[PDB]
Structures are given as C-alpha cells and as structure tokens.
Amino acid sequence: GAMVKKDIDDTIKSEDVVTFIKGLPEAPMCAYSKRMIDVLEALGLEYTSFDVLAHPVVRSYVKEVSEWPTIPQLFIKAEFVGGLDIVTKMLESGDLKKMLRDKGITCRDL
C-alpha cells in the first residue's frame, strides 16, 4: 500500500546504506544527486534511495528528522554521516571503505 513516514523510519533501521536525493537514482533532477549515486555505484554498494520530489512523506522526513542543512544526504547503519561535499573526502582518505569493511557492508576490493 501507500508509504507513510514510519516506513522511511523503519527502512533506515532495516538497510545498511540510505540516501535522500533530488530525483530517481537512474535519472536525478540535480547534479549532486547524480554525484552521490556515483559514490554508491562506483564502490559497488547496496542501498535504498529516497526521492524528495516524488513523495511529500520523503521531503517531510528530511524537514523534521534529517535536521542537517545540506542536500543530498548520506546515512549508514541508521545514522547520518554527511552531505555530498563530505562523502568524497572519506572516499579520498580511505575512511569510507574503512567503515564499510568494519561494519561488514558490501563493497569493491578492500
């Protein structure tokens, strides 16, 4: 049936990687949304991607619960990590592959 704000909240508890973006992950309506999905695809991860423009419940979760200013946003193991500006710095430093390998999350060759 229809998705309620509690289905996003239980999904953040269910999935190992979650993101909130401006579009579908295959056809985003923002360049930084393309660029976040390229972190998630280029490392070979498994994730759930939520579109704010397609459902008011998603943009409402971002308003009240994802209280950080920047869009788009990254979540790992039910916790907020950073915006698009920051995920690249973890990628460069190796700290992103370090967290994935420490938590046992799926990615490319360590």
Image (tube, rainbow, N blue to C red):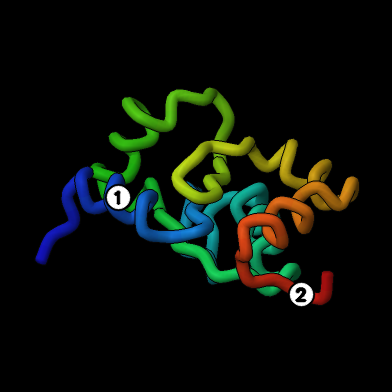
Q: Residue at x 61, y 38 (%)?
A: 81
Give how far across and how far down residue 24 sits, in percent.
Answer: 46, 63
Residue 90 shown left or right of residue 5 in the figure: right
Q: Residue at x 20, y 45 (%)?
A: 6
Q: Which residue is mark 2?
A: 108
Q: Amino acid at mark 2?
A: Arg
Residue closest to the eye, 66 or 21: 66
> In the rendered image of this protein, does residue 85 appear above or below residue 55?
above
Q: Residue at x 68, y 58 (%)?
A: 100
Q: Can residue 83 be seen in this snapshot?
A: yes
User: What element does badge 2 sit on?
Assistant: loop
Residue count near mark 1 (Cα–Cα under 10 Å), binned few <14, some 14–19, many ≥20: some
Give how far across and how far down residue 43 sits, in percent.
Answer: 74, 68
> In the rendered image of this protein, does residue 17 appear above or below residue 90?
below
User: What element does badge 1 sit on?
Assistant: helix
Quadrant where the C terminus lies?
Answer: bottom right
Residue 45 shown left or right of residue 27 in the figure: right
Q: Residue furthest left?
A: 1
Residue count near mark 2 (Cα–Cα under 10 Å), binned few <14, some 14–19, many ≥20: few
Give how far across and how far down residue 41 sits, in percent.
Answer: 67, 70
Q: Which residue is mark 1?
A: 8
